[PDB]
Image (tube, rainbow, N blue to C red):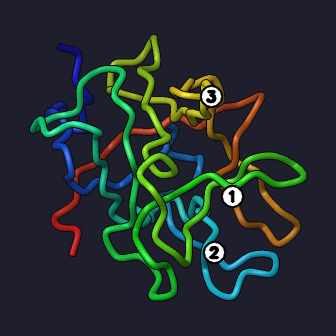
Amino acid sequence: DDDLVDAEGNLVENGGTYYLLPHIWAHGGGIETAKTGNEPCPLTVVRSPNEVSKGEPIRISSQFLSLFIPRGSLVALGFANPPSCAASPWWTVVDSPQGPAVKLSQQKLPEKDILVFKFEKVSHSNIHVYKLLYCQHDEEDVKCDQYIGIHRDRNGNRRLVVTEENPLELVLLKAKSET
């Protein structure tokens, strides 16, 4: 086993709630939502610009029943307290002209549209730091070949989108609670 480890050195709990913080202190705060484009409400998943903000507590749920999250496990990521307009907490990835973007949804999605993420251990770190991969279909299965990074839009929103150059790198900090 090489399970996911949180920021304090304890195994990440499956289904538990964590703050998804940048490894580099100066790179902003935790994850939250913004209302962008023609969205009717906040459905865009973004990173807070406030370095002191832990952002929202995020549920990290494996495809398995286990207590912890094994190496190479696909996960679904969801807001413990999502905007009222989202039908569920879960993040999904929606294609667009500029590329896949991380969003919330106004309907309930099938598990195959939310179990699309995987954390990947970053080499050369003392603290457990992970890149976040997006896993598209291998037309029957799934393949995690793209990374999530940030794209600051003309309004300053630091949107989580599929990236090419600089994957974000996070540390998972356990939250006092979710709900």
Mark closest to the chain's N terminus, 1 or 3? 3
Query: Is 39 positioned to the left or the right of 120 in the image?
Result: right
Instruction: Determine which residue is flagged by label 1.
Output: 159
The dot on residue 80 is none
Closer to us: 109 or 41: 109
Earlier in the chain: of badge 3 and badge 2, it is 2
User: CB atoms at circles 1 and 3 under 8 Å apart?
Assistant: no
Q: Give the vertical position of 95 relative to 34 (above or below).
A: above
Q: Are marks 1 and 2 in contact (CB under 8 Å)?
A: yes
Residue 155: give x, y in percent of width and height: 82, 72
Position of 43 relative to 60 (above/below): below
* Above or below, 151 relative to 78: above
**Mark before the other along the chain sequence, 1 or 2:** 2
Q: Which mark is residue 139?
A: 3
Quarter of the picture containing the N terminus is top left
Give the residue at the far left of this rendering: 67
User: Between marks 3 and 2, how big is the CA–CA gap?
Assistant: 32 Å
Residue drawn at x 21%, y 51% as measured from the top left: 15
Alpha carbon distance from label 1 to label 3 = 27 Å
Separation (CA) of disc 1 from disc 2:
8 Å
* Residue type indicated by callout 2: Ala
> Is 36 positioned to the left or the right of 75 in the image?
right
Q: Amino acid at mark 1?
A: Arg
